[PDB]
Amino acid sequence: QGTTYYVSSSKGDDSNDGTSESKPFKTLEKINKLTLKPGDQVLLEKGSVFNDQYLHLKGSGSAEAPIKVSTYGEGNRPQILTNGQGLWELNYGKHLDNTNHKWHGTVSSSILLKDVEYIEIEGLEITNDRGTKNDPEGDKAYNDADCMDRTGVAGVAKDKGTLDHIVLDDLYIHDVDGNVYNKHMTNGGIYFIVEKPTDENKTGIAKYDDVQIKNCQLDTVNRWGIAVGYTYNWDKFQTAELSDEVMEKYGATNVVIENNYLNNVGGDAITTMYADEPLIQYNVSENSSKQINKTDYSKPQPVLDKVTGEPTGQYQGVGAGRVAAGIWPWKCKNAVFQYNECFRTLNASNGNGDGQPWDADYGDGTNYQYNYSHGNTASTIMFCGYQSVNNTFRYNISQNEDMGPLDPAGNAGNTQVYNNTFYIKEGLNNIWHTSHGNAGPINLENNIFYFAGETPATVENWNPNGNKTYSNNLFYNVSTYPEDANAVKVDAGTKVTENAGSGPSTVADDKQARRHEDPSAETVFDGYKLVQNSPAINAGKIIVDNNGYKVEKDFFGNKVSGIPDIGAHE
Ligand SMILES: CC(=O)N[C@@H]1[C@@H](O[C@@H]2O[C@H](CO)[C@H](O)[C@H](O)[C@H]2O)[C@H](O)[C@@H](CO)O[C@H]1O
Image (cartoon, rainbow, N blue to C red; front, side):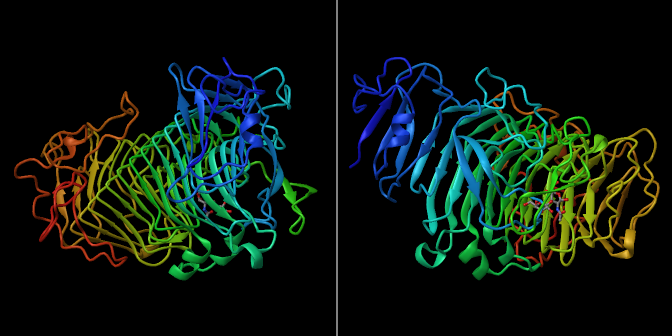
């Protein structure tokens, strides 16, 4: 079933019928005119270049016959170079969680999927660069507060109830030069939002089910890298605990973000929003928060009318929203982050109020497990504020962050950090964030605290706000110890791991996450494996995960049962 269409910037004529390679279309405007149907295909010729063009699709596939957008022929990825074209009217239909977040306006999107479901897009190169001749904003400054929002791929659910099955696979998205500031317009590489339906009684509550972003490479996109799920129904999630009933009715179900690479992201690299049990795995980010600094992020944003969303004449402090983390969830239920790498989340020293690789933000049941991080400008993990609850941070490896590993920034409830290995760079003399206050509780068990340096590190306060508990941790090369009745205290020169501090400082040449889930793997992380007679061996306690995540395995995929070793390796 369905019709295959062909488009060639090279060979095509828009007066052709576009249904054979011999008679292809010339411009994407021909596809934009169609109402697409189950089994339909849109094949862009390799070597093609669609300058000042865009795909704004209409129609929908079926579960058995999705629409496919893909390639034919041979040569370079077909290129969609939108250059500030592809205009459409974004309108959430009501203000967002902060009345200052912009929620209506004209947006430029290279690809727009608005109420298109059962669709798969693969193999394309996409840009939305501000640097060309006929660019609608001409020589407007890249960091003006009223620069138009820009997307590589924008998704909108609104007037078709639950949208099912949107797949973006192997897209190369670069030079999306969006608004430097705006968090919740479709503004950055890939951004999926949910708008208030015209008539919710008629079409049903708008939400997503089955959204797969996989094998994509993003470079120099702003503000967001990949964001999925910001919804008009944000006001249905204002409790600390998030019910399965709220999440299934209003939240994004079956969201998988996997095997993506991101470089030079202006703000946050990857964020799931209002998502029920999202899976975020095998992603690599480096050099994110590129524009979260006092040079780029330098112009004030308007105060918006709490009803109309129109500027009031008032302006915010330039610092508003001048924060970003690497790969993290917002108002998700039982989000799992596993097998990710995050390097150099930038700019905590020049106006980024955050800069952590990992941020268990407001939400319920976040589990970070079997992740690696290096050279981030803030602490390895933030637990953010009084609605960040039921947190598990386990079997992760962290080295050479520009702060100590822990940022419990006023988090609440059950917070468990266990079986991690933290390589703390020389001269930090702390395990805590340097300004967020460290007021929230943590239950700290079975962790390696490995202090690099020629002299023992000092830690002035092991128990800020009095609500830190410790059991069965290992402390290497530090001059004092917390209240841990089962502490393993280790002096400089006693080996604990094979080559502590020898984790990678850079992404793989092929930009893929280095797998470590089968313990027959030799990996670039093997310097964190325990030596024969390591003082970590058999010194941990059996963990009870009070968030309901049973202990299964270590960082490396070794089964864990009985009395565990201290740290990320069994
Ligand atoms: C509670 C808090 O302040 N969290 C910070 C995040 O800011 C929130 O982000 C959500 C995203 O959907 C909304 O924009 C909300 O209005 C913001 O309060 C922030 O994005 C992250 C990343 O730097 O850090 C937390 O500090």
